[PDB]
Image (cartoon, rainbow over all chains, first blue to last red; front, side, top):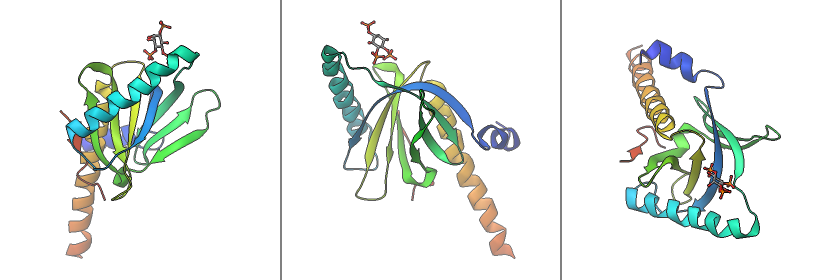
Length: 150
Length: 9
Ligand SMILES: O=P(O)(O)O[C@@H]1[C@H](O)[C@H](O)[C@@H](OP(=O)(O)O)[C@H](OP(=O)(O)O)[C@H]1O
């Protein structure tokens, strides 16, 4: 967890994670567990109902880096969603599902809840996000105390 | 539990 190793870990393209996009939903707050717990269920349900029509979630791969969270389509590699760190307000895992998590994107009054179904556990992704957020906060304080101590 | 981003905004 050395600031130096952690900075190397999120540098550039950062960490990659194979997953599927459950869905994107418009919410009202920038945070809250119940609110962000409910929205997950609403999205999984839309997905569940779609299975009857031979629907499938879009296979994607996502990156966690200083650019925030990016979602790339697995087939064409095209970047479909880029959510900068300062636009992300809340991270929340799914209690009844260890392979799914979500987060809220957007500026005040225009939030969105993104739901993801990871190939492996969602634990490592939540952890990386946590550390990346904390890191940036620290680097921002220190690199501010310095400029203001000029 | 969930985690809020300290640098949000
Ligand atoms: O075996 P079945 O009855 O076909 O059902 C599949 C099974 O539940 C997979 O685990 C799931 O992938 P995830 O675990 O990644 O959701 C897949 O979703 P998909 O069709 O959306 O890929 C389902 O279709």
